[PDB]
Structures are given as structure tokens and as C-alpha cells.
Amino acid sequence: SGAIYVGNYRVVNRHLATHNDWANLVWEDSSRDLLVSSTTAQGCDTIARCDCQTGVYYCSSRRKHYPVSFSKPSLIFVEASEYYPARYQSHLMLAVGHSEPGDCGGILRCQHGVVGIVSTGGNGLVGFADVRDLLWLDE
Ligand SMILES: NC(=O)[C@H]1CCC(=O)N(Cc2ccc3cc[nH]c3c2)C1
Ligand SMILES: NC(=O)[C@H]1CCC(=O)N(Cc2ccc3cc[nH]c3c2)C1
Ligand SMILES: [Zn+2]
Image 1 (cartoon, rainbow, N blue to C red):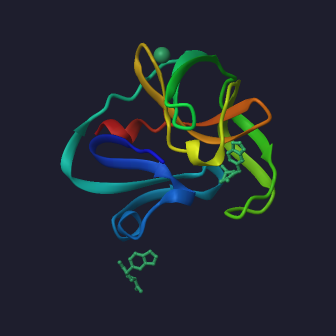
Image 2: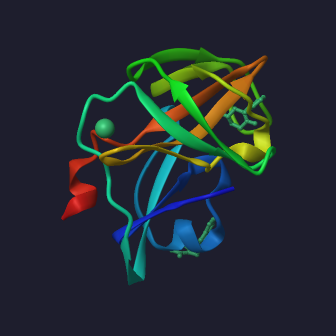
Image 3: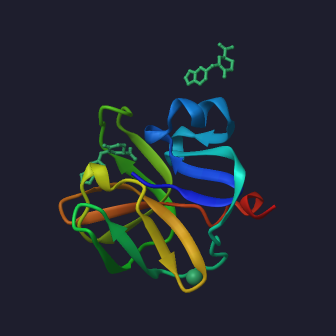
């Protein structure tokens, strides 16, 4: 679990969105595993606007933060799960690191701010849904 709170927006993994997220829906993209909902209270998380390929992510299944080198956002095949059939997930970045399904929502940050959230993993990999291209989150 986990979310990004920026301005009047809440960014979550689409597969973990709640009834309240869907009732206040702003945008969603199944191919990216992202959903953004509106909030009444202002958030002050900062989104990175950069091309960093290193950062640190929070891993809830270890209660620890880990440094990572990750790939640029790209279209990657993701095997079927109980939430999606087998498909290409877009805007996904991979890195070597520990992740389990419940780690989804952990934030990846660089020195500029929030880069994305954990969305995939397995066998010593961790995949993050990028949010740096969503410029409208800042307005
Ligand atoms: N026309 C309708 O039936 C909609 C209109 C807008 C609307 O908020 N709902 C209720 C609702 C809310 C969240 C969720 C998640 C899943 N289903 C939901 C249903 C019903
Ligand atoms: N973005 C997706 O399509 C997700 C949807 C929810 C989901 O359970 N998965 C499989 C998955 C996710 C993380 C991990 C870490 C280790 N094994 C994992 C297996 C894929
Ligand atoms: Zn950066």
C-alpha cells in the first residue's frame, strides 16, 4: 500500500484504488497501473521533473529504504495476476531490489522529488510506475 499526495490529488496504484478514489476520479490508466483522485486537503509532496535513473524506494516487506539504479520508463511485458490479464504495462521502470505484491505503493524518490510508485516485481526485481511525465499534477 501507499499513495502520493500532491496539491489536491492522490496518486495510487489503480489495482489498489478504493471506492472513494473511484467516486472522486480525475484520471486512470490501466496500462500504467495508475489512478489519480481528488482530495479536499492540500498535499505538499513534490514531483520530480528530471531524467534521474538512481533513487531510493521504500520497501514495506523489509521496513527499509533501498538505493536503486532503474531503467527509463518503457513498455514491459507483465505476467497475468488476479488484477490484470497478461499485458504490456507502459511507463514502467525496472530495478534490482526486493519486492512482494504488498509493496505496491511504496515511493521511489530522487534528489528532485517523487519519481514513481512500486507496481510490479518478483525474482529480485522491482518495477515502478513513473509519474514524472504527468505535468498536470503540479497545477
Ligand atoms: N452512475 C453510477 O452508478 C455511479 C455514479 C457516480 C458514483 O459515485 N457512483 C457510486 C460509486 C462510487 C465509487 C465506485 C467504485 C466502484 N463503483 C462505484 C460506484 C455510482
Ligand atoms: N502492475 C501489475 O500488473 C501488478 C498488479 C498486482 C500484482 O499482484 N502484480 C503481480 C506482482 C506484483 C508485485 C510483485 C513483487 C513480487 N512479485 C510480484 C507480483 C502485478
Ligand atoms: Zn531526479
